[PDB]
Amino acid sequence: MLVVPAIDLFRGKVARMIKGRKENTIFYEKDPVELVEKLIEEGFTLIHVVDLSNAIENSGENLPVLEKLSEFAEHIQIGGGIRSLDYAEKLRKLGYRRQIVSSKVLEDPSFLKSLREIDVEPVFSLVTRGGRVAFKGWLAEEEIDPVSLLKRLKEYGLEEIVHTEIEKDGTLQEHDFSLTKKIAIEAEVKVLAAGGISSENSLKTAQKVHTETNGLLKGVIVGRAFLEGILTVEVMKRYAR
């Protein structure tokens, strides 16, 4: 199973937004480029970097950092603001081969293919609250089961997702691995789990579902608990076999 450390970037710096909330913004004093080097040397193969300035702002402030993070791209999976092919190409040029996409794929599901013509592995970001897909639309977010969405995206060549329980991370709450398992298993998509990856009980559960699903659960993304020291590098690596 993969244990994937998460760094969020906002206004140049390492940031967390509590449950995605913009002025619930907190900044860490860490060098995102050194932290990434450190994570590399400690032996981590995958790292989740989200550009919070592109996703929320449509800003380019973090590009300088990604230009320098691009030393370690074959190791980094990048998200935030990837809504046009032109931008995806820039990233791919730097070496960024796994890219988290979302809103664009629901605007135009052919975006997945365009991304395969440029050796990008499109990773679809699936946010859910209370087990309900966080569609902007009313009936859509009430009625469309996660499985139903990804089953249709599968037809457009989708393979890998990140399933984020947005309202959990930034807190004690544990990730609902029952959901994630159902998702991985019924949609037959590879899943990285995010949100409420809070403690050791979570990696334990994750490992067990990583098994229950023949690896359809790739692993978890640790953001909150990683940066703050709840889960240390020692404890994380113990759970990546």
Image (cartoon, rainbow, N blue to C red):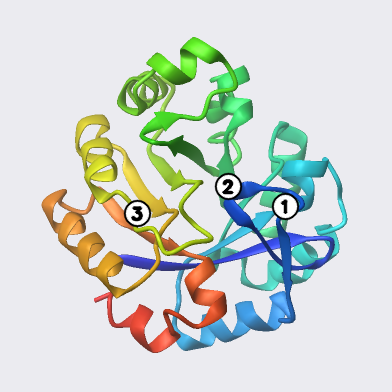
Q: Is residue 10 left or right of residue 216?
A: right
Question: Where is mark 3, residue-wise?
Answer: 175
Q: Is residue 41 above or below residue 107?
A: below
Q: Earlier in the sequence, mark 1 or mark 3?
A: 1
Residue 96 in view: no
Q: Earlier in the sequence, mark 3 or mark 2?
A: 2
Q: Is residue 108 left or right of residue 142?
A: right
Kind of element beneath mark 1 = helix
Amino acid at the residue labelled 3: His
Question: Where is mark 1, residue-wise?
Answer: 52
Contact, CB < 8 Å: mark 2 with mark 1?
Answer: no
Q: Position of residue 240 (x, y in %)?
A: 30, 74
Nearest-to-viewer mark from 2 and 1: 1
Q: Is residue 137 above or below residue 117?
A: above
Q: Quadrant of the C terminus?
A: bottom left
Q: Position of residue 84 (x, y in %)?
A: 73, 31
Q: Is residue 62 left or right of residue 213?
A: right
Q: Residue furthest left?
A: 212
Contact, CB < 8 Å: mark 3 with mark 2?
Answer: no
Question: Where is mark 2, residue-wise?
Answer: 99
What residue is rendered at 38% in x and 14% in y?
A: 143
- Could you say which disc has been placed on residue 212 in the image? none
Dot 1: within a 10 Å radius of its alpha carbon, few (fewer than 14), some, or many (20 or more) residues?
A: many
Identify the image quadrant of residue 183.
Answer: top left
Amino acid at the residue labelled 1: Leu
Q: Quadrant of the N terminus?
A: bottom left
Amino acid at the residue labelled 2: Gln
Q: Position of residue 110 (x, y in %)?
A: 56, 20
C-alpha gap between disc 1 and disc 3: 22 Å
